[PDB]
Image: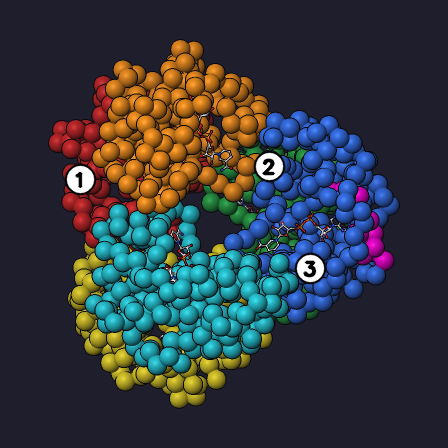
Chain colours: A green, B blue, C red, D orange, E yellow, F cyan
Amino acid sequence: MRGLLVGRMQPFHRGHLQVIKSILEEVDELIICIGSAQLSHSIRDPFTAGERVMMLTKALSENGIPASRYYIIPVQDIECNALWVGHIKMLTPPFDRVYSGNPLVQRLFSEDGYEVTAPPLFYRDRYSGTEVARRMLDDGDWRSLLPESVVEVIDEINGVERIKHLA
Amino acid sequence: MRGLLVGRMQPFHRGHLQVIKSILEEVDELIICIGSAQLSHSIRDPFTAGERVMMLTKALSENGIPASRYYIIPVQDIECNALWVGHIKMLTPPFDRVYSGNPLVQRLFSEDGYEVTAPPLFYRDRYSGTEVARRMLDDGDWRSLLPESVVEVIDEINGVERIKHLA
Amino acid sequence: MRGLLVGRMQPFHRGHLQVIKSILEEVDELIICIGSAQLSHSIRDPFTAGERVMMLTKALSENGIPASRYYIIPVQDIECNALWVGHIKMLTPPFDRVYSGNPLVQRLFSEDGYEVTAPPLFYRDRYSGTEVARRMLDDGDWRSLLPESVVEVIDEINGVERIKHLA
Amino acid sequence: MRGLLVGRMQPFHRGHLQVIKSILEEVDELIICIGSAQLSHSIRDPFTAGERVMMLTKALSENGIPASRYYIIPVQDIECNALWVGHIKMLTPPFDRVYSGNPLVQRLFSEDGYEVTAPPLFYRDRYSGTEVARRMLDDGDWRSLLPESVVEVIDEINGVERIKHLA
Amino acid sequence: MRGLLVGRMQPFHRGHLQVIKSILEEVDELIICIGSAQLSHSIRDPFTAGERVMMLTKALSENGIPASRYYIIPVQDIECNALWVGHIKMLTPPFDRVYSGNPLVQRLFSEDGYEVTAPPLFYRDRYSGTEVARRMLDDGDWRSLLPESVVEVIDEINGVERIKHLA
Amino acid sequence: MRGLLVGRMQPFHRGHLQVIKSILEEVDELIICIGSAQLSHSIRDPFTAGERVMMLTKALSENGIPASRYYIIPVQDIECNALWVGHIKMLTPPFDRVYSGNPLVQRLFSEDGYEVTAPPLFYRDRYSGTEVARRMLDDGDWRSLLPESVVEVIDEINGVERIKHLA
Ligand SMILES: NC(=O)c1ccc[n+]([C@@H]2O[C@H](COP(=O)([O-])OP(=O)(O)OC[C@H]3O[C@@H](n4cnc5c(N)ncnc54)[C@H](O)[C@@H]3O)[C@@H](O)[C@H]2O)c1
Ligand SMILES: NC(=O)c1ccc[n+]([C@@H]2O[C@H](COP(=O)([O-])OP(=O)(O)OC[C@H]3O[C@@H](n4cnc5c(N)ncnc54)[C@H](O)[C@@H]3O)[C@@H](O)[C@H]2O)c1
Ligand SMILES: NC(=O)c1ccc[n+]([C@@H]2O[C@H](COP(=O)([O-])OP(=O)(O)OC[C@H]3O[C@@H](n4cnc5c(N)ncnc54)[C@H](O)[C@@H]3O)[C@@H](O)[C@H]2O)c1
Ligand SMILES: NC(=O)c1ccc[n+]([C@@H]2O[C@H](COP(=O)([O-])OP(=O)(O)OC[C@H]3O[C@@H](n4cnc5c(N)ncnc54)[C@H](O)[C@@H]3O)[C@@H](O)[C@H]2O)c1
Ligand SMILES: NC(=O)c1ccc[n+]([C@@H]2O[C@H](COP(=O)([O-])OP(=O)(O)OC[C@H]3O[C@@H](n4cnc5c(N)ncnc54)[C@H](O)[C@@H]3O)[C@@H](O)[C@H]2O)c1
Ligand SMILES: NC(=O)c1ccc[n+]([C@@H]2O[C@H](COP(=O)([O-])OP(=O)(O)OC[C@H]3O[C@@H](n4cnc5c(N)ncnc54)[C@H](O)[C@@H]3O)[C@@H](O)[C@H]2O)c1
């Protein structure tokens, strides 16, 4: 039983982590697709795919989630929403369930015959990339919304410095 | 210490496996980039990125190589050889050494200031994608050139049937 | 005498139909280019090129307009407005007149030396893709703005279900 | 019952015509996809999609085949063979059977669950685009391999002049 | 000592000219990259790369700035901000300093290890492409914001006519 | 009177230089388009657009040809030969004559209504990119086929080292 989770992870936060945990309770393995892998250096998508790979790797690992239980696959976007599901399938291992709270993602996979599950929201109020960026720019408390290992990486790559320079 | 290996893995064979083993002897982790991830269904590149992801996953895992010691990242090709190194860097975690026997790959990374190591050849005669395909088409003994788990996947996806239909 | 009409047809409505009728009064044949053929599953452009092909086919046919009097050619968009006219010319048969109410379309074809005619508006108030979608989402009376055969197709492909899920 | 035929039609010849006729005997309508629509001005693919649209239109029409029995849809190629079937589906109306003598085309549609029929060859010896071009360049008798209306178009666009200048 | 200036030059105005002059005071040569070279016919980016090439050529030349002191290189945009610096480097001669008031441009080149200088603003209030277009559309006094030779070109290509038709 | 010359300049050799000289005898200015600007690091196209920009700049300049008499514009290739002429026009200043010995280039511009001149060959035997590369790889006398300033650049960028590593 292999599930699939698609997210930009800009950046990978506690919301993303709790849901990945819920999913690992009902699936043997989880394919984690880092979407919009070609985007970076924008307030909405500031980190590169590679940097996001490190964030998930350290977070999941520091959280005791075995490496053999997931796959981290960067996926660039394409112009045709109609071929997007096939695009994912071409780049990933087989999967039976799709987890997403994104309407377009859910609809596209539904039309394709896949069972789509919208995981429960875990403090959508504070645990959102929008909020994380919003706090970084306004000197708010962003570190609280992210796993410690994710904060460490953002520190090592000078994430905040980058984001502020862009705003 | 993190190294980087780039290969099409069409398909992942014993040659690829032994070298990955040699590299794991001098590096803590290895980033395995499945190149030409957008190519499939051709005699030269018959399997999709996703199918190749399964091949490496089962092989490495069946060979007792811990999941935490490597990253499997599919990478599509781009039109400019000049930006290809940056393209890899954007999609991967940081790395210190590059392993490749491909002249273009070696040169591009050299020009970029990376130390490039050309791993020793392990029976280049039989352990080559060219040979594997050559034997599949001519009913030769291809199973011997591939890890058992890789043969199993090729069986489950009907690889041989596909390749023959294409030739 | 062959004219050219360019439109997204998202979806094909009574406005599009009346104008196609006006044009067939002064031209032997009409080339109908379904623009933005690569877009789908968005509130602005919900249907695929193929689905739109069916809409026009059934509508025009049900309206007694002979098949030999028009060509339905899907056309994807390109990044350079400067080459867009050439892009259309490359994919279509020769034509003498261009019909459009779109400023960019008109200007581009003018600069290219083509006579451009802005057909008269037929109830632009209700006969607009914006309005059709607006009514589908708010349970309004959309069926009235579309040819019956177009409503039938939207029913057979579950258009409304899709659009609502996206909003 | 709607079938699908995919071909470059470089140019549309008697071979293509007879097979389209055979197919119309067992299907209500035929979707004719002009593949490699982005290619032109090469010995292998000398005519543009638009020019090929005219060739099929005049040929089929001059042969008494009603316009309502087919769709002519230009289709550009894409880099991923894995998404090519979806690419066609996105741009065309629904279809039940696929006709092709091309191994890749057949395999791709098979893997996708479509019944694929390889139509019988009608003088593959002389009725091939390779041969048509071969004769045009060497002043051979090419006109015999093509429908009269197709010869007329090639004359009106100066096809032979173009091809020779390229060789 | 070779510097690099990146700008859309939509259109090339007095602001762009004064800064190019300031830069020529501390650098032997200046590489002038006309960015977004693939964009044209939009209120934000109305002129083609070629038209912009003429604007800079006449302006700089009419201003007595020797041709041997600069390079005018059109540069199309790419989807990955992460490879954009490499993209510029691939298309230009070597350079030591980067001049820009654009946050993204500055940040990207900084991350890449280049010294970035934000030239002083010269009447940013009136000397902006936004303002030039704003005045052209509202019959304002745009000619005052542009070098005379630039006005002449805009006259010869019917710039104002184009822009108004688009708005 | 402005002419247009299109060439890959891989690398810029004495053949390219003499012809540029012949053209400057009958035209006020020459637009020199460095084609295939996206290609590099291949035996056929080893240098980047930027490196080629330096080659032409030093060569032309060292040959006393005033900078104001030419434009050096890098041009990436596109997939549709049908839009290629428009692609060039979009990126360059206006021009009246086209100079090329390339059949495709000549044909495309002819079809577009431009007068095309095939300049006389100047020792096509030795003055060809094929030959230059052929000699670099086989330790032949390549320096003789290139302007001195071009040899200097190839030395400063380690051209020979690169090419050999690729072969
Ligand atoms: N190229 C295409 O045509 C196409 C079509 C569809 C989608 N996409 C891609 O999909 C990606 C977008 O993913 P996204 O916007 O959903 O990313 P995201 O990171 O914002 O969301 C990822 C997942 O996290 C969940 N999540 C976030 N915060 C949560 C919280 N506090 N509690 C519980 N769950 C929470 C969301 O519900 C979602 O399932 C992009 O890369 C996009 O480009 C591409
Ligand atoms: N897009 C670009 O501009 C660009 C530029 C360069 C390279 N690339 C990509 O690089 C990839 C090509 O990789 P490749 O051709 O080397 O793949 P490959 O699978 O043939 O080789 C991968 C590695 O395996 C090693 N290897 C294979 N058999 C071996 C054996 N028996 N013993 C020891 N070592 C062995 C090779 O030396 C090499 O380092 C493609 O995806 C290509 O497109 C892309
Ligand atoms: N790729 C490029 O560079 C580029 C440049 C220009 C245009 N395009 C394409 O052009 C297409 C846009 O076409 P559009 O926005 O006009 O589509 P549309 O469907 O909104 O309009 C199509 C036509 O219908 C007419 N029309 C609509 N309702 C009418 C009514 N009630 N009465 C009378 N006439 C009515 C419009 O005036 C227009 O001529 C897109 O595919 C766009 O991407 C592409
Ligand atoms: N983009 C992608 O990934 C991808 C993948 C597969 C195919 N394609 C496209 O498919 C198209 C290729 O089609 P093709 O090469 O088959 O074109 P073609 O014109 O050579 O052949 C078209 C059809 O005509 C039939 N035919 C030709 N001569 C005949 C004769 N004398 N008697 C009977 N039948 C005859 C062939 O069997 C075939 O089914 C291209 O556009 C190609 O790019 C694209
Ligand atoms: N493709 C990518 O990923 C990517 C990433 C970054 C940037 N870009 C490109 O960079 C280009 C954008 O350049 P831009 O928006 O800065 O162009 P612009 O023409 O608006 O500005 C160019 C320069 O002029 C200066 N300037 C303008 N008016 C001035 C005045 N009155 N006084 C002093 N200085 C003045 C600006 O500070 C800037 O350095 C685009 O082509 C964009 O696409 C591309
Ligand atoms: N993207 C497209 O669709 C498309 C279509 C056509 C051409 N192109 C581009 O055109 C470029 C190809 O140019 P090319 O192959 O001619 O480059 P090239 O450098 O080989 O030749 C350039 C010019 O030099 C001349 N020349 C070379 N040696 C000479 C000598 N000894 N004496 C006299 N004249 C000599 C040739 O006749 C030619 O006019 C490429 O960038 C190609 O991609 C692109």
The answer to whether residue B66 is magenta is: no
Q: Residue at point 20% right, 72% down? A: E151
Question: Which residue, given by chain and number where applicable, does mark 2 sit on?
Answer: B42
Question: Which residue, given by chain and number where applicable, does mark 1 sit on?
Answer: C97
- Quick one: quadrant of the C terminus of chain D? top left
How far, Cα to Cα, is label 1 from label 2? Answer: 44 Å
From where the camera sits, is residue C143 visible? no
Q: Residue at point 26% right, 47% down? A: F111
| Disc 3 secondary structure class | loop
Q: Residue at point 58% right, 44% down? A: B38
Residues at circles 1 and 2 in contact by the CB criterion of under 8 Å = no
- Give the letter of the chain under mark 1: C
Q: Position of residue B46 (x, y in %)?
A: 63, 37
| Disc 1 secondary structure class | strand
Q: Position of residue F7 (x, y in %)?
A: 39, 61
How far, Cα to Cα, is label 2 from label 3? Answer: 30 Å
- Give the letter of the chain under mark 3: B
**Residue that protrudes farthest toward the bottom in the picture:** E25
Query: Which amino acid lies under the numbered mark 1 shown in the image of this protein?
Result: Arg
Residue closest to the eye, D129 or E37 = D129
Give the magenta range: B12-25
Q: Which mark is residue C75?
A: none
- Give the letter of the chain under mark 2: B
Q: Which mark is residue B93?
A: 3
**Image depth: mark 1 or mark 2 in front:** 2
Residue closest to the eye, D148 or A6 = D148
